[PDB]
Image (cartoon, rainbow over all chains, first blue to last red; front, side, top):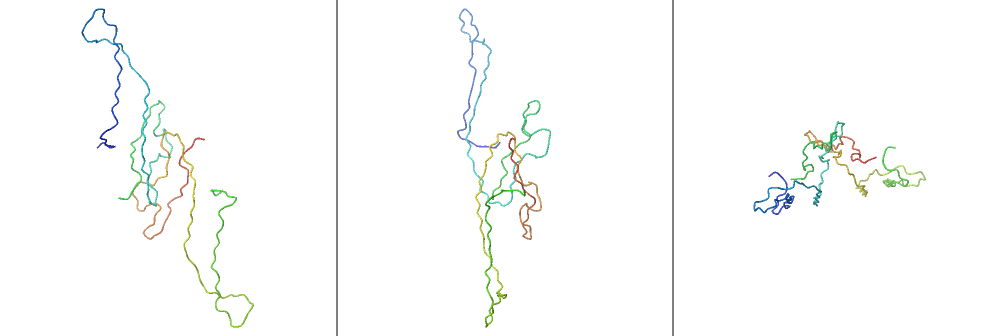
Length: 103
Length: 103
């Protein structure tokens, strides 16, 4: 209901964890669980590649369609860009429904 | 300078004429040119087929382009349509320059 593709078998959850690295243990054995660890974290790169199939528009409509367009007029910023502080923003929601089809 | 494709050898001129059909000549010979003809005209269909080659847009631009679009708001007529008397009209000139390229 929030929109998109209902899947019986969706893309799987991908789970990641830093492996615990104990700190120095005591010199005599204790059966108590280790509470003492070397503080650490991890970083890397992730890539996602998705192939999408397209359904082409077959229309015989004579007159021009409504299209999504950026405003041609001047402004202080460009839509869907960073500002002078480096903050990327999205000016508005963009749906998918522009082209038309007979009912 | 009015725009378009300069051609050394353009599409040729296609010339058409109704063939003259004399009216009834006099019963004695005259060498004078016929001035008297059966009035007629012609009608038919004409087809023109042009193949156009396209140059695709390769851009890496991140933000959306300016696009030609029809206005989404309501109005009394639809652009590029006939009116209630059957008169087809063109609301405005449409150029070709919307997509962008680096210089």
